[PDB]
């Protein structure tokens, strides 16, 4: 329904690396549209090792992102497709990943619950447009200058109406998606539960001390992570519902937003 707006290549100045991976490379940049103020942006491009199926995946990523217009989803500013290299220009998120922040900064209980509700709000919007993310984790949520949390990285997102390989993030994946390859709105919900666990701990990996095969066997047999010492009991209740074995009993993101919003203005 929506479409990426094309931007003149000469408006963009690429400045410095924000993050590199197998996916490609994200740069910090600036966009100087004539008669408008200069703004910081992020520019995502392809590995120097090109392949035309990778150009198409990047353009598909942009089209998915162009459908989103929400305060808790990283915004699409436009694309540069005439010429080479190709750039997808996105909103710049000054404060980096949610993961790095909670690991390295002091955060209050009211911040922890608001960030949780903000991510649920962004995922609710994604689902309400007919998509599933399939890759949610705290390293994939970014923080703006106002410390507003926003869902990023749509590399693996797919229309709901319809995996990677040895890179499967086992610690964030629901049992049914590991065993039967069934990805759905309710496996996104399971992953959000694990994200909440990350928000309330300061370790790098959930299930610390277990490898990936140990995690899978333990979780399919009914193990669940216990309540972090610094997590309020009403919050852990919500976290726990995201991990019910039967996916149909897990709440929707619309329900999660509401439950979290009630605690967000709770004094206790």
Image (cartoon, rainbow, N blue to C red):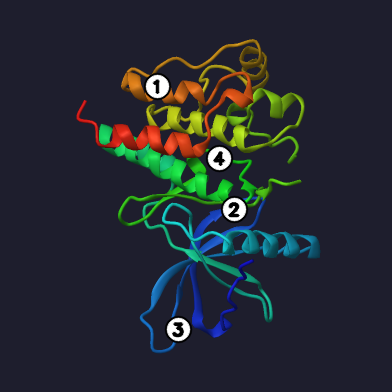
Q: Would you say the residues marked 4 and 2 are in contact, meaning their CB atoms lie under 8 Å apart?
A: no
Quarter of the image where one finds residue 107? top left
Q: Which residue is mark 4?
A: 136
Dot 2 or dot 1: first in sequence order is 2
Dot 3 or dot 4: first in sequence order is 3
Determine the residue positioned at 66% across, 15% down.
Answer: 220
Quarter of the image where one finds residue 55? bottom right
SS of the residue at dot 3?
loop
Q: Nearer the viewer, mark 2 or mark 1?
A: 2
Q: Which residue is mark 2?
A: 129
Quadrant in which the N terminus appears: bottom right
Visible residue check, residue 235 = yes
Visible residue check, residue 106 = no
Dot 3 or dot 1: first in sequence order is 3
Q: Residue furthest right?
A: 52
Give above or below for 123 relative to 54: above
Q: Residues within 10 Å of mark 1 (few under 14, many from 20)?
A: some
SS of the residue at dot 1?
helix
Distance from disc 3 to disc 1, alpha carbons, whole Å, reads 46 Å
Q: Which residue is mark 1?
A: 236
Distance from disc 3 to disc 2, alpha carbons, whole Å, reads 30 Å
Dot 1 or dot 4: first in sequence order is 4
SS of the residue at dot 4?
loop
Q: Residue furthest left?
A: 267
Distance from disc 1 to disc 4, alpha carbons, whole Å, reads 19 Å
Q: Residue furthest bottom?
A: 35
Q: Nearer the viewer, mark 1 or mark 4?
A: 1
Q: Which residue is mark 3?
A: 33
């Amino acid at each position: 329904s929506k479409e990426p707006r094309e931007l003149n290549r000469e408006w963009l100045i690429v400045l410095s690396e924000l993050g590199q991976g197998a996916f490609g490379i994200v740069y910090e940049a600036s966009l100087s549209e004539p008669k408008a103020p200069e703004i910081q942006v992020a520019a995502k491009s392809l590995r120097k090792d090109a392949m035309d199926n990778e150009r198409e995946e990047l353009l598909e990523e942009a089209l998915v992102m162009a459908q989103m217009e929400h305060a808790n989803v990283v915004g699409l500013i436009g694309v540069i497709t005439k010429g080479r290299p190709i750039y997808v220009v996105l909103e710049h998120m000054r404060n980096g990943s949610l993961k790095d922040y909670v690991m390295n900064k002091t955060c209050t209980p009211a911040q922890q619950v608001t960030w949780s509700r903000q991510v649920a709000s962004g995922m609710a919007h994604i689902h309400s447009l007919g998509f599933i993310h399939r890759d949610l984790a705290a390293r994939n949520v970014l923080l703006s200058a106002s410390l507003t949390a926003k869902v990023a990285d749509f590399g693996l997102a797919r229309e709901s109406t319809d995996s990677r390989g040895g890179n499967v993030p086992v610690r964030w994946t629901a049992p049914e998606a590991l065993e039967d390859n069934i990805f759905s709105e309710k496996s996104d919900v399971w992953a959000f539960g694990v994200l909440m666990y990350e928000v309330y701990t300061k370790a790098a990996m959930p299930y610390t001390g277990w490898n990936n095969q140990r995690v899978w066997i333990e979780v399919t047999n009914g193990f669940r992570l216990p309540c972090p010492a610094d997590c309020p009991l009403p919050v852990f209740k919500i976290m726990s519902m995201c991990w019910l074995h039967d996916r149909h009993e897990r709440p929707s993101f619309e329900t999660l937003v509401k439950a979290l919003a009630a605690l967000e203005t709770d004094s206790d």
